[PDB]
Image: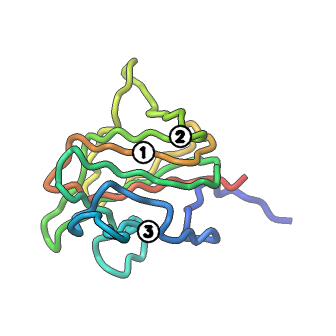
Amino acid sequence: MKSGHGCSEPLGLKNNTIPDSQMSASSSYKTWNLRAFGWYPHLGRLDNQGKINAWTAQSNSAKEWLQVDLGTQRQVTGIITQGARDFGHIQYVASYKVAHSDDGVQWTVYEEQGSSKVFQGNLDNNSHKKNIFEKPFMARYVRVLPVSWHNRITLRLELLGCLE
């Protein structure tokens, strides 16, 4: 005799508990890639044990890109972003092109201007920004490529779903 109002669920902070195999970027502030893992992504998650609570870039340039591999094909009904800082200096990305792919070949960048407008917005580091189910759909892998950042490429991108 219950009902399900909430439609925006996490990807590893409820039941899925997805491990460190969901997010992944070219390189992080860590140092580089090389053999083994190298990067230490998957910080966007809340209740961060460390402090960063957000993935940063390596070359601190536009050549860096953050992608998310799911391989589970789930329908998303929202999103959420959060910036980070450097033990004091507040950093956050502004202009960034984020596209989602369900089959892997079709990268939906979500145009608007008429051609292919990128996703702009700082939202600071101490201010999270989520998006309602303005246009839900199944996804298997998403790609993000930041162009205009502020201070340093330190942010976190998370997608929410309905699980229905």
Return the x and y of residue 98 as percentages of the image width and height.
40, 41
Reading the image, the residue beneath label 3 is 45
User: Which mark is on residue 32?
Assistant: none
Q: Is 61 placed above or below 56 here?
A: above
State the CA–CA distance, disc 2 to disc 1. 8 Å
Q: Quadrant of the N terminus?
A: bottom right
Kindly report which numbered mark, 1 or 3, lies closer to the viewer in this rendering. 1
Q: Is 1 placed above or below 71 here?
A: below
Q: Residue at x 62, y 40 (%)?
A: 137
State the CA–CA distance, disc 2 to disc 3. 22 Å
- Residue type of the residue flagged with mark 3: Arg
Kindly give the residue lying farthest to the right in the view shown: 1
Reading the image, the residue beneath label 2 is 101
Reading the image, the residue beneath label 1 is 143
- Residue type of the residue flagged with mark 1: Arg
Badge 2 marks a residue whose secondary structure is strand
